[PDB]
Every structure is written in C-alpha cells, then in structure tokens.
Length: 398
Ligand SMILES: CC(=O)N[C@@H]1[C@@H](O)[C@@H](O)[C@@H](CO)O[C@@H]1O
Ligand SMILES: [Ca+2]
Ligand SMILES: [Ca+2]
Image (spheres, rainbow, N blue to C red):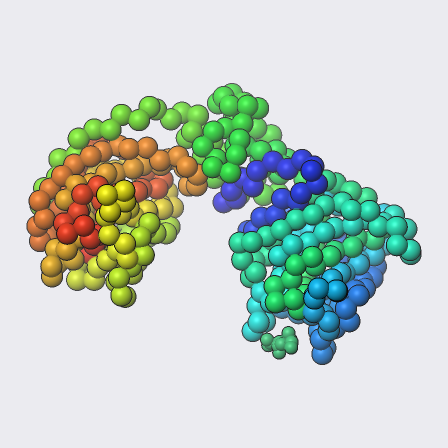
C-alpha cells in the first residue's frame, strides 16, 4: 500500500517523493481521472540540444524505456532546461519524472530543479512556481508536488543534474488530487507516529476512510489508514518478563504448521549493524540452522545490536525463537529486548518483553505475553563476546 508523503503547502518548496503508484494495477484508473493526457501536450523544446538520437520528444512519448539526453551538459555557465507547451492553459500541481532508464540509468537525474510558468506561447515571461530537490536516488521515478498552477508553458530547469548530462525518460503531468493530499496529511510529520488533528479520533478516521472509498487508489490507502488506526488505539508501553529456554519443537513440522508464522509472511529484514564477511542478514531467516548472519558492528558501551523484521500481515506472537552461530556461539543474545510495532512504517515501536539466557547451542525461545506485530525489532541488550549472530529467527503464535 501507499505511505502518506506529508502535507504540502507553499516558501515554494516542492514535495518530492517516490512514485510507487506505478507498480500498481490501479495506475490506469488513477491516470484516467488525474493525469493530464499526452494528447494535451502540444510540443516540447530545450536549450541544450540532444545526445545522438536521444531526441527531446522521447521525454514525453509515454515510454519510460525511451529517453531524451542533452547534447550539452550542465557547467558553471550553462543550465539545462526543458519547456513543455500544452494545447490549452492547463492546471497542474504535479510532475512525475524519471531520468534515463537504460544502461546508464540515473545519469542526468534532476537532483535539484526549478519549475516556471507562462500563460503565453512565446516570450521569456516565465515566473517561478516551485523549487525542489531529491537526494534519495537517481534511479527513482519521483512525484514532484507543488501549488496547483495554470500553465500554457511549463519550464523545467536542471539546477543540478547527476553527472551534468541532464536526461529525462518521461515528464508526466497531473491535476490536483485533493483526497490524495488529505491522505498525505494523515500524520503530523515524517515519523508518522502521531495522527493529525482532523483524523485524531476513530470517528474522524473511519469517516475519512469512508470518504476515500470511491477513490481510484482507495485500496492503496488502506495500509496508511490501518496504521493511523493502530496508533489511535495503541495501549501504553508496559514491558513484561520473557521466560527463555532451549527448545526443539522447530523440528516438528505439524506443530510449525499450526503455531509458527509462515516464512512468507516476512516482508523484509534489516539490522542496525553491518555484517562480517558474507554472513548477511537474509540467512537469519532462510530456514537453515547452518547458515547464520553475523554483525558488522559489536555491542559498545553505547551501542546495542538490533535486527528488524517487517511482516506482510499483522500477527499475534507469544514466542520468538532464535539461535547464535552454532560453531562458536559468538554473538548469542544473552539478554534480549523485543520491540513491537503495529504499523507498517513509522517511529511506532514499543518495548514488549525482556529476558536473559546463557549461551547454548540449538535454538532458544523467548516467551512473552501475546503481542500484535506488524514489525518486530530484536535487540541484543547483552550478547556473548559482544558480537551478534543469528542462525535462525522464528516467530511463534499462542
Ligand atoms: C551508455 C552511456 O553511459 N552513454 C553515455 C552517453 O549517453 C553520454 O552521456 C556520454 C557523454 O560523453 O557518456 C556516455 O557515453
Ligand atoms: Ca520516453
Ligand atoms: Ca539460517
């Protein structure tokens, strides 16, 4: 699902975020209502010519796999710009843009940009609409969001282009989507751990959900709405004590079928350290007691190792089963801190359980009270030899 991008009002700094909507089957439906049709894009020009056959028209041909590239890169004296002319004066609030997507994908990405408007067909009467930047990645298809503005001509300036050779796979234009912008303001800030005032009760939130039901990408809003709901209904952090002990029931296939969360419920895994050699994080969840992750950063006086696993579906767990590397036992979580989040994204973790067990071969369970998990954090509060290793990390239900 979609994650709220934060509210934008403009001073005139554009909100730039990854355009994840492209990976959805709802795109055609969304484009139907909000996209400025390509048939409305009359013509295009630019001030820097073109490299080889990467002609400027290829920037607005509706094909992400064809690109324009400038013939003259940015330097101290020259800034690449593109000017799109529309059939009629068109109200636009968003540009969806990608750099070239060939073998040199990302090269020429508009790391910094300015957007200008003209209501006339000719002459330099352009006024500045919005300035923006995107530092995350050069390879991304990004949504650039600014104040809804009338354009006969839209000028896009490559204030900073990655490696100077400005490129564009596509420039796409969208009309204002008020409900989408309402969704984007669901949380107070980028940490998304506090619901905004206009949705800060279940009554308000549920009514908002109902308001969105006819929206073409309503299905993609559900995750964010559920996230807000989880926050609104969250109970105070009251960590219990986890009883740890050696177990062997992981061998029991039938038992696993009933009580172990399916491995395919794991959306992603990450950790706060790196990893020593080729003992990467993914082999902590490969269902192989012989392969193990090892940390690339040991437990300092000010540092604990912690591993984070995201789930597709929220699940209620009472046990987390783990083991160290079986050769040495170096990195056995002698003392464990377990954190639960009921949201898919955001700074919404809370401590649920604490426990300790001596370093031992095999697998160890950490049994606590039934807790809901959308994501889990496994912290090495105390570890053997100050390292951190996991051969397997498993999640068991009550
Ligand atoms: C494939 C590839 O990277 N091609 C690029 C080309 O598009 C242009 O940017 C050129 C500038 O000298 O550098 C490379 O050859
Ligand atoms: Ca193209
Ligand atoms: Ca493993």
